[PDB]
Image (cartoon, chains in turn brown, green, orange, yellow):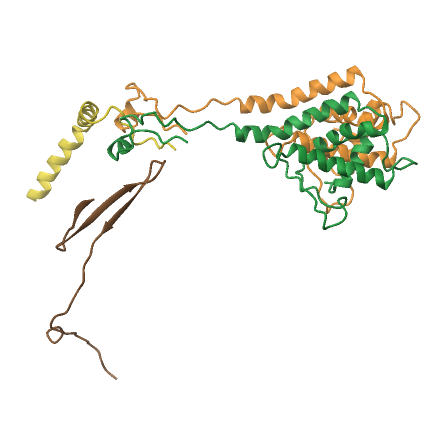
Length: 53
Length: 152
Length: 152
Length: 45
């Protein structure tokens, strides 16, 4: 297992690798855990042009 | 092809032997034909040793469908001659007969040709032993820590 | 060629065997003709192992065509002798005869000549192994980074 | 006239003129420092 940083966004996840049995192959997983939250829904907004009829 | 049934194979074998054909005035008994079909089935099962012998595509009849004769043998176009030549050679002793030299040679040639393709397919080389290194010229394997062959 | 059909091939084989020819006083028997045609079809199928055997140009009849006899065999001019000599040798035991030494020798010679060109064509050399360098003499490949043969 | 065009033209001329020697030198460095099996264009099974 290794640390694995996503560029641009400021997040760090894991990069894990395991090997199969009796064969030259393996599995690789790039996992990363996050949850997006809106603490002030009244502060966010939306713009909707052309909302006629 | 005009030989599409086990009974057709038996009739061809008998014609090759000279015992019965479509031109003779005396024909063999249906009991004799059934015995020849039993021989053909037994010989084919002996050849096809539960899938680990001479693969030919022959289809083994079941007892639910009553008559073995009348079933398609399923052989490819290039197996019929070998099959019925060997069958004639095998059923020759039934009639105090002896298959001729041409029939025997053709049976041998046909059996060899039948097994040729299966032998070519089966001539497969075993994998590397479990103790052989993969060498450092295999860059990705060396980096990813597959330093020895798996084997098996 | 004046031998243009399976019937001509069968008639030539029977004449060579002495079964039915104008040299004797016998005509070709209609029931013998069908069996000889079946034997010829089986022998062509056994030879031509679905493309991996002896290539001759023979055209295999289908179920739709009513008479097996009458179709052009499609053989080249250089295979007729081999085909009908082998046919005579194969269908001799039907009449409890034995093909003579000249007929057998001609059949062997014809089959060898039939496979000569195909053997020459298949005498091909395997490509270079993928672990062989191209050598620094091959300036084009070495500049283009082809330091080893592609193989396969 | 353009400074960028003149500089790029000169650089392109030199880079293309000195290519073969550079490729041979890079191959020598790779062979002597990484691995003697410079076999990446040959597609084995």
